[PDB]
Length: 300
Length: 237
Image (cartoon, rainbow over all chains, first blue to last red; front, top):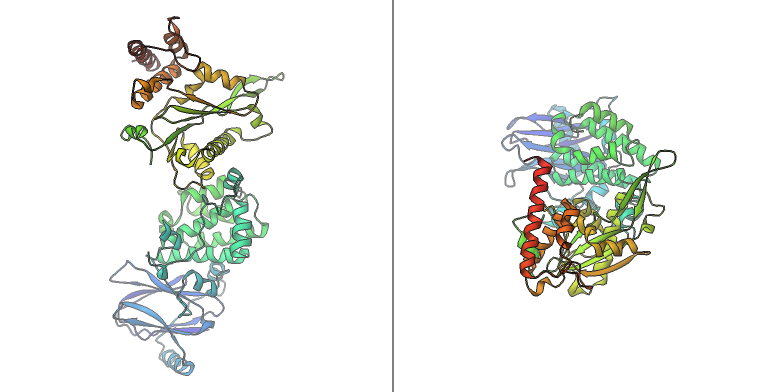
């Protein structure tokens, strides 16, 4: 089990750790989060009490180093930092644990929610969607734009998601215009899976990362990316059976986790109706279709 | 974006543009089979591609052979239309290629946009105008060349005949839309109006009769009368 210690909590803030969240008061004696499960990527996120705008946060993996949070009163945010001095870090964490100034990552033993949401998410790939190579962790916030958004303006502070565009020469083979537009199997299987992602695991990894950026930060470009990656599979007549079965499980857990009140802004009516009712895969997403019908029948 | 009654004059500026109408591309007769089921028999069609400034009509004849062994023909028709418009643009020299293509039906936007990805600088646009281009197959010489085609064929016309010698393209287009609207609302009455007086003939190289300016005013008046009457009948007002 790993620990993300905090120097202090000088400003009142809602702290998120994965799907959990805690309120911390201005100057509350808070020194961080312990018992974090090793072997998963994690996100630690923040919404200031004084500014319910700018949700922001840090993707990290505890196996990649010793990370802590410290408030910066110049930039006005909780910053993730790496401590390279192993002994100084173990010594700081042990003191804070002894004085019980840390909240415990509150995992239920039965509960596989975080694993199911992050199954294909790999910290090494995140660092290539969010290029800040001097850090082992990745900052994301509500306002960050995608590379594809910046096409249609600061490239260093952008989300470098795989560009998907159904009305593109990349998506449409010369002389297969109608075939490739109505059946995107060639764009999915040859261009995207074989050409760019190499395998379905990396495709699902970016899809799961886009969803989580949309849910935790309300990042609009992330939402667009999540829906684009779903729509490319649902609009393909020819998808490996294992990809459809896994996609069904991935989406089921995403729909299960989505706050009930955020369905109006985080779910694209057109994409879901297409996937569940119109598309080649209308009969292939049993779990996803049952939970969507029982939880958001309005949207459909 | 979309073309309407406010940006109507744009049709007659010096930017090359084409209207595409796909309403006569896929044409069927519906009939009873021996077992008393219903079947369609396709008949020859046409893409109506018109430069509204010059009157140049690129009539691509769609021979029934293009549908042989194909499924979802109403959907294929839109993509076949996009494919032929694309091939037409690529066959034109650069300085003759349109800067805009206006489709009369919104269902053509994605088929044409995907077929024209190679031409990112050509704007594909819908219109809110209810243009009567479907009535093109009520023009006898256009109907005749379509029905006689034994193979795919492109035939070039000027749908304004020699009108631009005497009137502006704005007036030429308004005369064309009024003739086509008449033909669409009541073909028989419209065609009776046009051919009543056998001393006014159609030149071999024309589609419409050789009316003097005065006879056009009378004809144009008779077409408006036809259109308003039928409207009163349709809607009992």
